[PDB]
Picture (cartoon, rainbow, N blue to C red):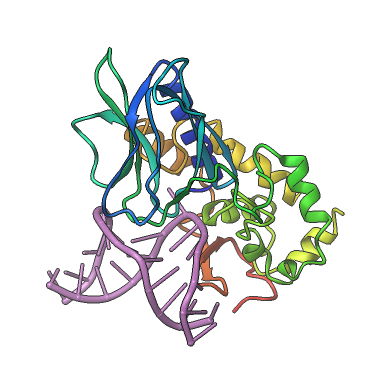
Length: 270
DNA sequence: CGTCCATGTCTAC
DNA sequence: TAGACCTGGACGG
């Protein structure tokens, strides 16, 4: 998952858990290296917000719930496979690694953090990752300024296909979005990032870093992902113009990750 | 059986 | 920077 997936996951949690009351402990699969979540409430609601490639749950005990408890924030990163799913308490998926259980009345449900591969991670802090750039979806002006102010940074020596994955400046952009973005402007992926950015100091590279992932969010669906039917997944595959599409060339950036492009690879190519 | 590939970090050398 | 962290699917023989 990349920014749009984290965003729709946030929306999924909020819409699904609007009318739900949770109760009891927050349960961790005994194979997850991530920390135990010390939290018990007789009655609590669950809300979410997203910032680039991170999502924040807030667990909010209701009035008079017991034990006396202050709200608790957890921040998730999903790595290659994470996901959130509302399931029947007795049909936990394989790889439901963290699990929030509905109190009665109503049919017993588990909001599960599902992460097949265990590249996902969570922290008790409630805080966004120190160093991560602003969210390209929700802090666009902040995102734009945070780049143009810092072209001096060695980050921008790298080729543009590489800089776009540095979450310090492009929080929320990942390997499908970088491909999709450059294709829209036909910027060679191994053009030097400083050259392409110095220019702006008919939409431009930074406009698209916002608007292109925002197109994924406005499919509905779960962006690149199977939930909301294996119907919405094909609605994404049809949106894609570059990433994996027949006809397109592809190469490995200096860190093994595959960039899909059309035509000219550009000057700093392997 | 086997090999390779996948929406991302994270860290040891 | 090579390597680690993981599982499973789409392919090969």
